[PDB]
Image (cartoon, rainbow, N blue to C red):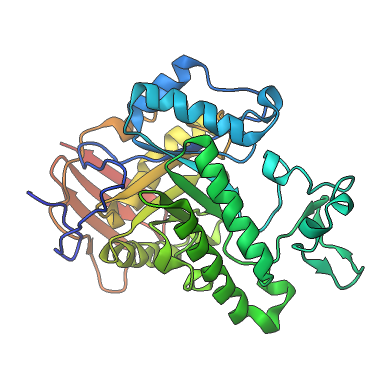
Length: 360
């Protein structure tokens, strides 16, 4: 146990700028924001106790501070006051031009025409010859090289201005379904944009891509340091998808990269805190079956500060310890999986949705 071991027994060698990792208890990642307010010191303390790795969300502190990147700057400093080594990521979406940061302030129905260069970065709906939009939120066009340059510089500027340790990039699809004949170009362009960002952030900055395990992100994945399994709907929590997760988590770890295995019980088949606490054992088990060095669990029922980050799920605080080996698929075509850790025995049936972790 001198070095962290992937489930294939190979050694995981982290980069110097990675967050802390340990198997002592479930390795945790947190991600949260609140448009309406900053964290109270007591809330910073609560989260800081439970994680070394978090991300501030897309709108945090927008109302009190006026711009979401100042929310990120505020919390990054608050957390680092407590744990100077905490890793705090700045959020930026690669697809939706959410107008929550100063950087994106022009991407509104009433301002965009006054910014013709920024407007030219956006997808046009061929059905209207006007900007494509989702409730008047416009769509970056990754096929536009000037957008790739602007966006990657902007994100790097947001990481620098906020004092964050890197970036969480949301979305990898580049709206490929809107230009499906160019899907391969979109995937290639996305990789180009991420490589620009990775370079522009300079050394020692973490790049986490959301859902970057998906084939659509293959050109982006190499320059990423981390990828998140978002489990954003029921299909992604199927027994087949969970087995794919576990396969992907090994591949990610073998690449020296980190994974975030994120669960929002809003996507559970079944009052969210009660449900979340009841399902914690099952979803933790799903993570532990596939867990690797420098993989982290995120748990709650959404993305707001009030969506789980400030609740105690006692399973997450129990001693876990290093895995004693890879999971065992109890029968070759069945959906029961077990795995042993130094302080816990995991059993899960992903066909039926039942699990039991026996804490020793």
